[PDB]
Length: 141
Image (cartoon, rainbow, N blue to C red; front, side):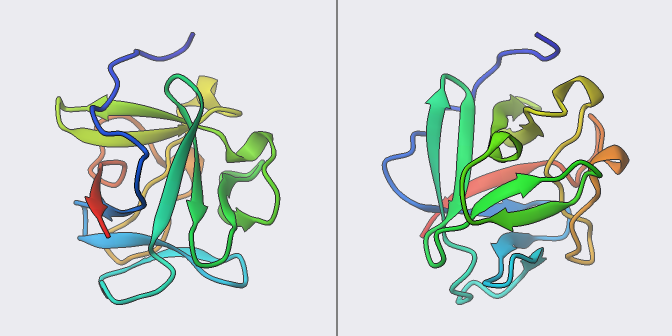
């Protein structure tokens, strides 16, 4: 147990967009497996469906392509065709308001899903508690 257990209130009944308040980008998983952010709300690759594997553990998947968000051994986000250990994230409340996603596989190192102000994904080792890059708000589709 390397992290707290304050959980966000939402549910997974419907798909969502994951809005990063850092630069205001929506998390995007492209068909080729590339992950980045875009401010275009009409983009067809920003609609995501979360699901819970265990309480507080989730998969984040592209509704358009079926790919799972995953963080590799060097901290890079990618789209995975099949669910594996790199696809599980610890979903937690942060600052009594936002959702954060910590790589379960690399939880001891505090590697988060995060977007920089320019829309590029932040590599896991570059993320850490206290940054704006790691703060997301799940919006309806």
